[PDB]
Structures are given as structure tokens and as C-alpha cells.
Amino acid sequence: STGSATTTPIDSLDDAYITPVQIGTPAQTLNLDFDTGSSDLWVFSSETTASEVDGQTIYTPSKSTTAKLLSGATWSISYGDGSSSSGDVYTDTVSVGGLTVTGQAVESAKKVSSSFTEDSTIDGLLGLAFSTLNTVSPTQQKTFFDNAKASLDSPVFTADLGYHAPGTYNFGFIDTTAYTGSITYTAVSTKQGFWEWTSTGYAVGSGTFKSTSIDGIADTGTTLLYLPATVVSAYWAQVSGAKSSSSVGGYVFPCSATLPSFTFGVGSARIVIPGDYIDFGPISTGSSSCFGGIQSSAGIGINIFGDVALKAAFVVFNGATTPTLGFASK
């Protein structure tokens, strides 16, 4: 089997991408944030504290004839700075573009943190990291991809995110018309539960490519590109007036600037992120100071190849017995 679904930016800045997902019988369609950096499929629901729902579409398990409460099971995900989302667990039928998994664990939120309430465009998350990170207790549950894997024509999914435009998630096949040239595959460490790999280096604009190993994760659930401070300084040095601001919490640059591209290495191949992808707009409405899309990973503990990087590429998440990651230009 295979499935395909269009993923769409939630706003004019590509702050995140939502993909429609059918849950239950009859289907309830929720717009989920497909997240290769986490491993829980969790949703706003009829059980979510009423004052914490503000425009989101909810899953109502009592209206699904295939929903079954997973007895005694709970989940909780904590955020590095902001509270937590948590709840109970059902099993139900989940389909993405008709690709169907029966008995998928669907984590129903009883509480969500404030940032989720405040974002009416995201009805929940569909995790696509490795199932070792799934938070359900006392019985860990499998991701949608893990449950689908054996049925798929190939045990793979691909991310083709758009800049200011819709994109595609495909499961089970490689659309060879979606990229240019060849796909370069690179090794993955699954020990931390992420799609963790090593970039071979970087270049700023038309400058010299610097060969240096950059370990990090391919994370569709993170907006920006987080890299070591030396790399980030080399990039912003090329933007007149750009500087790291402690109060804002990262690099800002004059909105009038024209940003250079940024190139990252995958083996001997090169992925070029156009400068326009690095502009995240005014720090506050009406400001002429803009927020950069490449930021230091210093406080994070890991480098993150988030949407700013991934949307420049066609990305293959190969879940074969030894997983690998593929990148092609597009």
C-alpha cells in the first residue's frame, strides 16, 4: 500500500505545516502537525479542558464506533520552557490519504499548554520519530508510520515541504518526479530516538564551502534551522546590521536586507536554502527589525535541521531495518 497527503503552511511565514488526517468512524478530519522530532499522535478532543480550546477541531471518541479506550494508559509531553500537554489514550482507525492503520493509539488531550491553545490552526501532532520516544504509559505505543510500515510497498515516507506554498507527504513510495538529480543517502543514529545524521559542512551565499561534521536531527516539527554558533555567526556576518539580541532571543536583521543563501552538505551533495527562506519577518507588528531563520543551537543541546532546511530539499525518511535519510535538490 501507499498514501499521499498535501501539507500546507499554517501562516504566511511557514511557521509550521498541517496535514489533514482522518480519525475514527465515521471519519473525523483533524489538521495535524507531522513531526519527525517526536513520536506521539495526540489530538485536541472532547476531553480537553474547555478553556484550553480556542478554534481547534476536536476528536470526539464517543462518536467513533471504532474507538476503544486503552484502559489505564496516559501520556504527557513536557516542553523545555512551557508546561505540558497530557491526557488519555484510545485506539481507533487513522488514515492519511486513504493509507489506513487500524488500532492506532490516538492520544486524547485533557490539558494542553498555552501555546497550543493560542494556535487555532493546529489540531494536534502526528509523530514520525522512532517509537522509543512515545510517551504512553505504562504500555508504550507505536507511531502511525511504525504501524503502517509492514503494509507499505517500501518502508519509507518522504517530506516535500513548500516555501510559502503547499507540499506533500508520501508514504510507501518515492516520487521520482518530485526532485532534481539524485537522492544522496546518509547514515542515521537512532539511539536518541531521532532521525539523527551528520551534515558534511556548509557555505554562506557564494562563499567557500567549509568541510565540518555537523551532527543534528531532521525535524519537520521545528520551524527554524538551529546550528552551532560559529556557523550561525558566519551566516549573519554577511547581512549588514544583523546581530544576536538577548531580549528577542536570537539573531535579528534589518527587514530591508536581502539575505544570502545557505548551503548544507549531505555527503558530497549540497542543498541550497535560498535567502528568502531565512526571513521570518518583523519581530513585532510594524517593526523594521526582522527575525532570522537560522539560529544558534547553543541552548538546545542538539542541532536541528528544521523546516527552513528541510523545505529546500526532497527528504526520504527510510525506515528499513537500518534506517537512512535521503536528500535531493528540487
Image: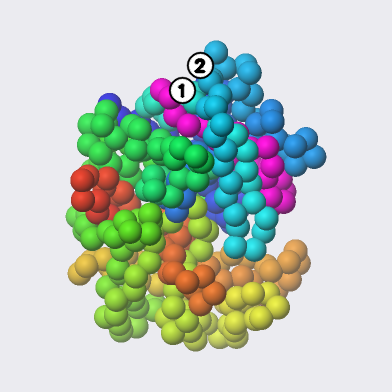
Q: Which mark is residue 93?
A: 1
What range is drawn magenta here? 102-124
Foreground of the two, 84 or 227: 84
Identify the residue at image location x=68%, y=37%.
110
Q: In the image, residue 79 lies at what x, y percent?
A: 60, 57
Q: Sequence-wise, which precedes: disc 1 or disc 2?
A: 2
Q: Residue furthest right?
A: 51
In the rendering, at what x and y percent does residue 248 appear?
68, 74
The residues bearing labels 1 and 2 have C-alpha atoms spaced at a distance of 7 Å
Is 312 situated left or right of 200 in this image? right
Where residue 274 appears, as percent x and y from the top left, is 42, 66
Which residue bears the numbered disc 2? 66
- Labels 1 and 2 touching (C-beta < 8 A): yes
Q: How many marks?
A: 2
Does 79 appear above or below 117?
Answer: below
Left or right: residue 20 versus residue 99 is right
Residue 181 can be seen in this image:
no
Q: Tell me the kind of residue under disc 1.
A: Thr
Q: Where is residue 176, by image quadrant?
A: top left
Mark 1 surroundings within 10 Å by alpha-carbon count, few (fewer than 14), some (14 through 19), many (20 or more): many
Q: Residue at x 27, y 73 (%)?
A: 200
**In the picture provided, is 22 more to the left or to the right than 289?**
left
Amino acid carrying label 2: it is Thr
Percent x, y for residue 22? Answer: 50, 26
